[PDB]
Image (spheres, coloured by chain):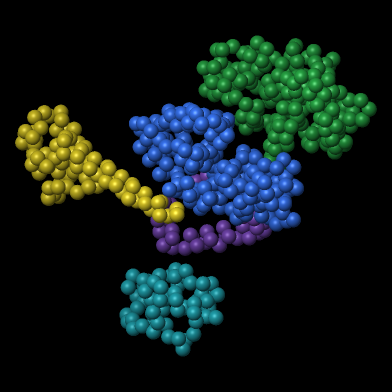
Chain colours: A yellow, B blue, C purple, D cyan, E green
C-alpha cells in the first residue's frame, strides 16, 4: 500500500528517525496489541505505521504522551486498586 | 501425645518472624499443619516439655521436635519435594544458603536493635537499613526475584522482613523505588503469602 | 515423573509425601492417567506422536 | 449438535451409574438423546450429566448413526 | 585453585580440614597469622572471618556452608544420612554442640580464671553423658563415621590444652572413641604442627 516514504518523511525531516519512530509504533500493533489509528486495508503492521506518520497523528513526541499518560493511569490503577488491599485487610 | 498422628506439631509464634518465615514454606508445599499462635511468657505445655531448648517456632513430626528457623524450613524442603524451593547445582545452591546467612546476621540485628535501641539508633539503624535496601535496587530488573527465576527460600527470608517495613517505622525514599516497590507487588500477594499471613501482622499494612 | 521438577521419585517414596502410605499411590496415578488416555483430553497430546 | 457424536464414556459419567447404562449394551451418545426411561441409585446420575453439557431425554433425532 | 584461608589453630579451621582431607579434595591452604589472616581477604570476604573457601568462582564463610558444600558436591564417601528423616537428626545434633559446648569453651580460654572453672566441671559431667552410649555404635550415633562426629574429633583433640580430662569414669566407654577416630588417615593427615602440641598423639 506504501511504495515510498517521501511523504511520511516530511513530518520528520530525517530518514534515520522515521525508521525509529515507526519501528516502535509498529510494535504496539503487534505485541501488546493496541489499535491502528488509520483504517487498515489488509496490510502489514509496518506499512500501517508508516501511514500514520504522514498524517501527523504519530511522531516522536506524541508517541510518549500517548503512553506515559497510560503508564501512570495504570498507577491510577495502582492506588485505586491499592484500595483493594486497603479495604481487604481491615 | 503431640506426635501421636502422622501430623505435624508447630508451637508457632504470632508475631515472631521465625514462625512467619517458616509458615510460608510450611504452607507453600500444601501440607495440613496445625497453627498455635502462642506467647513466650505463656506458650502451651508441650512447647516447653519436649522442647529442651524452648525456641519459637518448634515443629514436631512423630520422632522429635525440630527447633530452628533454618533446620525447620530445610527439613521440609528436603522431605516434601514438590514444588521445589532450592536449586539443584551445588555451586549455586549453597550460595543460596549464603544470602540467608547474610540476612540473619546482617538485617536481623537491624530489627532487634530497633526493638531495644536508643532514639537515634532506631533511625540510625533505619539509616543503615533504609538506604542499604535501596543500594540493592537494580537487582530486581534482571531477575524477577532475588537473582533466581523460581520462588526460592532466599526470597522467603526477605518478604517477612519486608512485611515489617513500616511496622517498625520505615518508608522508602529516593530514585528507583518503582523498581523495588513495584517488585513488592509481585511477592506480597501470593498464595504462599496471602493464605499464610497472620492477621495480627496485617493491621500494620494500612 | 520429573515433570517441572528435579529428579523423579519412587512410588512409596511419595507415600511419605501424601501421608497415606499404601498401594493406593500405585492407583491414583493408575486410574487418573487412564483419564488422560481417553480422547479429547489427548487430542493435543496425541499430536506429537508420529 | 457437535455434542452427540462422542464415545459413551466421554461424558465423564460416574462409573457404577456408567456401568448400569454401558453394561446394558449401549452403542453411541447421539442415540442417548433418544434414550427412553422405560428401557432402563441410578437415576440421579444420568440426569445432571445430560442437564449440564446440553443433552436431554427422550428427544427426536432421525437418520442416525451413518458412521 | 581450591584455596583455603584456614587458621592454623582454631577448631573451626580444623573442622573443614577433616572434611577436605577425608573426601580427597586437592586443596591448598593459606595460613592466618594467629587467627587473623591478612587484610588482603576483605576483598573476597567482607567479614574477614576464617575459615573461607575460594575455588575459582565461590566465596563462603561458615563451617555450615563450607563443610556441607564439600559434601553435596564431592559425593563419596558420604557424610550424611540418605533419607530425610535422619538428616534433621544429624543436621540438628550438630546444632546442639555448636551452641552449648563451643561457646561454652569461650570463658575457658577467653574468660578469666574464675569462670574457667564455671565452664570446666559443669561441662565435664556432660562429657560422660553420651559416654555409656558408645556401647551402641562405634562412632557418635553411627556405625560409620559421618559429619556429626566432625565436630568432636577437632573438639576432643583440644582437651589437654584446655584442661578437662578423664579420671575414673567418663573414660571407660569414652576413650575407646578417640583411640578409634584419631588413627584414620583423614584425621591423621589433617593434624598440623601447631594443633599437635595440644597432646602427645
Left or right: B47, with A84 as reference point: right
Q: Quadrant of residue B97?
A: top right
Total labels: the figure holds 0
Q: Is residue D63 visible?
A: yes
Q: Nearer the viewer, residue B193 or E13?
A: B193
Where residue B194 appears, as percent x and y from the top left, is 48, 51
Q: Is residue C2 visible?
A: no
> Where is B27 relative to E122, above or below?
below
Q: Is residue A80 left or right of residue B61?
A: left
Name the outermost residue toward the front: B119
Q: Nearer the viewer, residue C15 or E158?
A: E158
Percent of width and height locating residue E80: 70, 35
Above or below for E111 versus E125: above
Point 70% across, 14% down: residue = E8
Q: Is residue E136 left or right of residue E54?
A: right
Residue at 51 percent across and 72 percent down: it is D14
Residue D20 appears at what percent x and percent y?
53, 79
Query: In the depicted view, which residue is nearer to us: E111 or D18?
Result: E111
Q: Residue at x 86, y 23 (%)?
A: E165
The residue positioned 52% from the left and 59% from the top of the image is C33
Q: Residue furthest bottom?
A: D38
Q: Quadrant of the N terminus of chain B?
A: bottom right
Residue E44 position (above or below residue B54): above
- Residue E154 on image: x %, y %: 75, 23
Amino acid at each position: 500500500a506504501r511504495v515510498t516514504v517521501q511523504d511520511a518523511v516530511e513530518k520528520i525531516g530525517n530518514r534515520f528517525d522515521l525508521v525509529l519512530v515507526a519501528a516502535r509504533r509498529a510494535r504496539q500493533m503487534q505485541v501488546g496489541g493496541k489499535d491502528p489509528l488509520v483504517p487498515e486495508e489488509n496490510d502489514k503492521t509496518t506499512v500501517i505505521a508508516l501511514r500514520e506518520i504522514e498524517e501527523g497523528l504519530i511522531n516522536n513526541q506524541i508517541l510518549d504522551v500517548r503512553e506515559r499518560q497510560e503508564q501512570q493511569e495504570q498507577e491510577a490503577a495502582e492506588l485505586q486498586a491499592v484500595t483493594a488491599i486497603a479495604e481487604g485487610r481491615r | 501425645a503431640a506426635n501421636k498422628r502422622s501430623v505435624m506439631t508447630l508451637f508457632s509464634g504470632p508475631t515472631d518472624i521465625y514462625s512467619h518465615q517458616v509458615r510460608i514454606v510450611l504452607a507453600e508445599k500444601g501440607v495440613s499443619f496445625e497453627i498455635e499462635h502462642v506467647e513466650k511468657d505463656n506458650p502451651p505445655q508441650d512447647l516447653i516439655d519436649l522442647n529442651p531448648n524452648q525456641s519459637v517456632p518448634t515443629l514436631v513430626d512423630r520422632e522429635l521436635t525440630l527447633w530452628e528457623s533454618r533446620i525447620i524450613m530445610e527439613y521440609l524442603d528436603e522431605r516434601f519435594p514438590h514444588p521445589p524451593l532450592m536449586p539443584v547445582y551445588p555451586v549455586a545452591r549453597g550460595e543460596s544458603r549464603l544470602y540467608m546467612h547474610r540476612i540473619e546476621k546482617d538485617w536481623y540485628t537491624l530489627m532487634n536493635t530497633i526493638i531495644n535501641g536508643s532514639a537515634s539508633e532506631a533511625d540510625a539503624a533505619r539509616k543503615q537499613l533504609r538506604e542499604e535496601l535501596l543500594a540493592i535496587a537494580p537487582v530486581f530488573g534482571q531477575k524477577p526475584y532475588f537473582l533466581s527465576d523460581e520462588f526460592s527460600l532466599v526470597d522467603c527470608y526477605l518478604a517477612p522482613l519486608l512485611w515489617r517495613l513500616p511496622q517498625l517505622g520505615i518508608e522508602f525514599s529516593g530514585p528507583g523505588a518503582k523498581e523495588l516497590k513495584g517488585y513488592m507487588t509481585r511477592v506480597f500477594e501470593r498464595d504462599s503469602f496471602l493464605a499464610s499471613l497472620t492477621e495480627a501482622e496485617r493491621e500494620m499494612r494500612l | 515423573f520429573g515433570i517441572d521438577m528435579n529428579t523423579d521419585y519412587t512410588l512409596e517414596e511419595v507415600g511419605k509425601q501424601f501421608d497415606v502410605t499404601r498401594e493406593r499411590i500405585r492407583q491414583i496415578e493408575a486410574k487418573a492417567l487412564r483419564k488422560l488416555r481417553h480422547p479429547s483430553r489427548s487430542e493435543v497430546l496425541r499430536s506429537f506422536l508420529d | 449438535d457437535p455434542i452427540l457424536l462422542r464415545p459413551v464414556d466421554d461424558l465423564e459419567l460416574t462409573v457404577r451409574s456408567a456401568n448400569c447404562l454401558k453394561a446394558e449394551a449401549i452403542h453411541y451418545i447421539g442415540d442417548l438423546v433418544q434414550r427412553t426411561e422405560v428401557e432402563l441409585k441410578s437415576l440421579t446420575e444420568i440426569k445432571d450429566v445430560l442437564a449440564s453439557r446440553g443433552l436431554s431425554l427422550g428427544m427426536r433425532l432421525e437418520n442416525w448413526p451413518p458412521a
